[PDB]
Length: 57
Length: 87
Image 1 (tube, protein in one colour):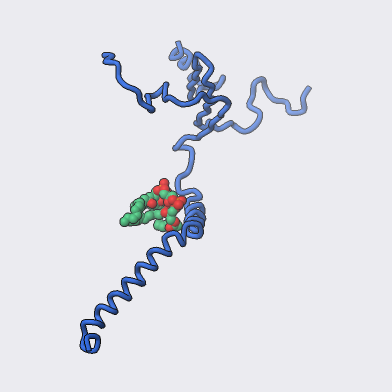
Image 2 (cartoon, helix red, strand yellow; image 1 turned 180 degrees about the vertical axis):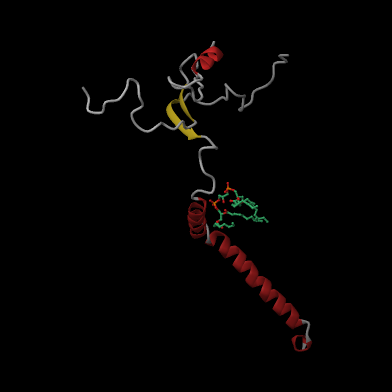
């Protein structure tokens, strides 16, 4: 067993900081154009998980 | 609509009439995450110093010559119509 006797799925390290930005990898030969837009979500242990799932639905 | 317009060199968004680009990655941040008034004074001072040292004489020479001939003309015109100038 590991020396650091923790639980399952516990965070290990600093909480990452969500940094709004943009990346554009232009390519004029592609007939289509794929775009992904996202905001900060909810963690596994957040008490507003199923609400986010409901909004996604 | 239609109306079969003419030929231009601007177009619009989506088809701007430019050469095809490839492999140009671009990153930028959010205005709420970056900090205004960061490095403004240093960069502005360096740019102003470089511009003064670079362009410089291009403006310095003609304006200086014009001012010199202005002063000389005023002095000479004042002298000539005075007492001793006409003699």
